[PDB]
Amino acid sequence: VNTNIASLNTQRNLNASSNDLNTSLQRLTTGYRINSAKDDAAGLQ
Amino acid sequence: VNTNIASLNTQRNLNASSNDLNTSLQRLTTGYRINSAKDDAAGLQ
Amino acid sequence: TNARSRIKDTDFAAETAALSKNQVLQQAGTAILAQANQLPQAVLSLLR
Image 1 (tube, rainbow over the protein chains, first blue to last red):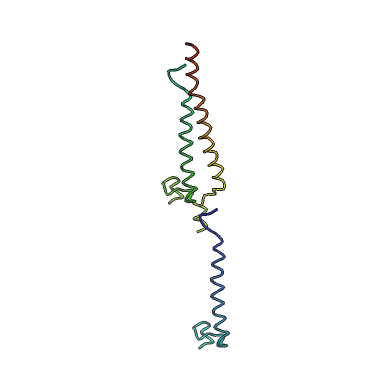
Image 2: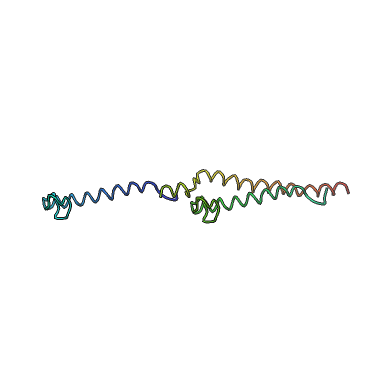
């Protein structure tokens, strides 16, 4: 079949993966598991 | 017999055939089984 | 989107077979006509 590719579902998953990847790298750079970003704002506060 | 040819009935069938043929080719070009035409307007809608 | 294809996306792996059938019919009924239109010719050529 040609009209589209259901396997773009694969793509979606990778977008999530890359998001996680980048955030992990941030945490690995600074050593701060709570980014200076809002994320987990409780511990941040 | 000569006054006419009952076998023109064959012709009629072919007209239908060619109609189907053309529509199939349209569906095969775009990959859309529902032509942009009205045909099967429910699924179209 | 997957639904949109289940609506639109022709399973042309079947419609290919349908396609051949139509092409096939064009060919066949045609050859039948090439035969059919020889009938009256024969009828009169002989009765004369």
